Image: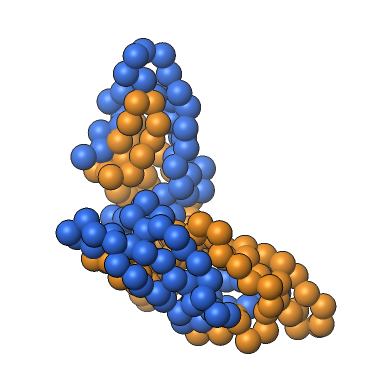
Chain colours: A blue, B orange
């Protein structure tokens, strides 16, 4: 998996975003970015791999009620099942701004 | 923790982003957004809490070499330590575009 560095150049990291110019199959290049915040997590001071998002394996995300995030997500078996999570668990209103805690 | 829904309204989810209009302490409101992709992960078809990013607890992120993400991250003890992770582990160049896998 991975190995982007072998066929890209001018890579850079700003905040949580990686940007790089990479070779296309038919030749030529393309510059793109990827937000890692959603991949990499801090576990007791050490950066560890998680998934890079959940939107890559889940679809039809919706706000159910006033604080429930609902979606259809893929299982290890590659099948979609219904799931939900209460955003009130960790999303707070800090003086008018939504913040994770 | 959390409980944003109690003092906000007009909440909505689009993709991985939650947007809501929330009450400020001094009165009045503010509309803000938060990208959950970095919080919530899909574990075998079930949405689970992770952290919402790593940029909230890590600082001085830098690209070391051609594929290493380096940063100073907080431990459980609230102290900053040096850490790094090889982005080549999971970031690939798919026909010119950076993608997690």
Q: Nearer the viewer, residue B25 or B14?
A: B14
Residue A46 point in image, percent of width and height: 31, 60
Q: Is residue B23 visible?
A: yes
The residue depicted at 72 percent of the width and 67 percent of the height is: B31
Q: Position of residue A49 (x, y in %)?
A: 28, 55
The residue drawn where x is 32% and y is 18% is: A25
Instruction: Identify which residue is drawn at 68% across, 73% down.
Output: B10
- Name the quadrant containing residue A40: bottom left
Q: On the picture, is B61 further left or further right than B100? A: right
Q: Total number of numbered labels?
A: 0
Q: Pinpoint residue B15: horizontal percent, then vertical percent.
A: 51, 57
Q: Looking at the image, can residue B80 be seen? A: no
Q: Quadrant of the C terminus of chain B?
A: top left
Q: Residue at x 53, y 71 (%)?
A: A63
Query: Which x, y percent locates residue B84?
Result: 32, 49
Q: Nearer the viewer, residue A76 or B31?
A: A76
* Picture layout, residue A73 above or below residue A21: below
Decide if residue B44 is on the left or right side of residue A60: left
Task: Please tell me whether residue B5 is drawn above or below residue B79 in the rendered image.
Answer: below
From what the image shows, is residue B19 above or below residue A6?
Answer: below
Judge by depth and name the residue closer to the eye, B13 or B39: B13
Q: Residue lying farthest left?
A: A77
């Amino acid at each position: 998996l991975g190995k982007f560095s072998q066929t890209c150049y001018n890579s850079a990291i700003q905040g949580s975003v990686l940007t790089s110019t990479c070779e296309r199959t038919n030749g030529g290049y393309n510059t793109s970015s990827i937000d890692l915040n959603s991949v990499i997590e801090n576990v007791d001071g050490s950066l560890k791999w998680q998934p890079s998002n959940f939107i890559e394996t889940c679809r039809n995300t919706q706000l159910a009620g006033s604080s429930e995030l609902a979606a259809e997500c893929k299982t290890r078996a590659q099948q979609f099942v219904s799931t939900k999570i209460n955003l009130d668990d960790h999303i707070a209103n800090i003086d008018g701004t939504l913040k994770y805690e």
